[PDB]
Image 1: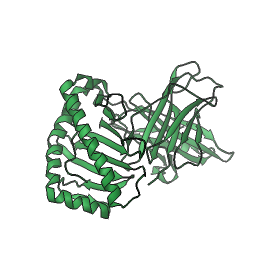
Image 2: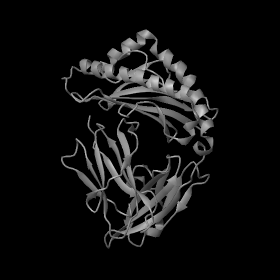
Image 3: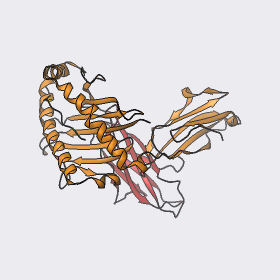
Image 4: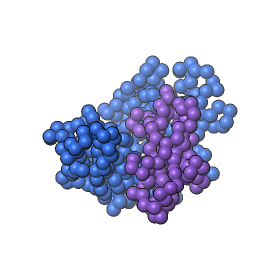
Length: 9
Length: 99
Length: 274
């Protein structure tokens, strides 16, 4: 449900 | 950026002396998130006040609900005191039974 | 009817006072249902609506791990932003992220979101096509180039059109009898002499859910939006909301004004007066 951001800023 | 808090003080249910209710202080539209909010009874800080989990709006500005159970009387005065980086001194908003 | 699943995430650095505070809250429509707070005794995703108490250990462990992975991403992102904006260190900064999905009548994806703000200003946002990014300034164009070369957007599109909408549908199932209910507003008009010349008419709307509502004052069938003082919708604390809209009119003319209320729980809008 929650999802991670893949690439770095 | 800095946005000063909007502040509303009010009860959960229509107030009636002798009837338990909840006193709410709703702060919104502010940024950064550090903010200090107290609920006062006759000028004195009330103790068991809780708050909602930090959240924010479409414009990224924050909002929180501080609240405590209580039983209003015709004479006891209630208020919300807020300090924020944008305020040069605490802002005190009295609880108006008709607002 | 439309519904949404949204997460609001905030990371705030506190130089010299520890690692950044990291908080995540999730909502289905206007009902909060989970939270993760890095400053809790035992940081983990926890239910904040009674109907989530139905999810088992495996749901909470996975959610908690996604939160902790995202927490480190924010520690890195606060440092990177400070470099991109060439800011002095020692400053306390804020990174925010909002992501989620709105679905339509067929409870299929209608709008997917994944966007960010730095120190309260837009930084970068996934566009409605779920493929491109809108960078808010030059620093964000740097981030935009990196994400456009990865194929980063495709990943979010798959989650927004899939897992996001499937979990929202699951949540609506779990809390159905409270999430799909409405509480139509209980409204009334109060009267407040201001001078001996004019009076304040205040239209109140209490105990409603969902939060979206339109309160309007009219005179001779025309909207008085230009004269209205409208406070922001506020939580009563019991899952319901309140709002009021006021107008200052001439004494003895108060019977000319009508308050109009529209809300999902009102098949026909209300029309009231003092």
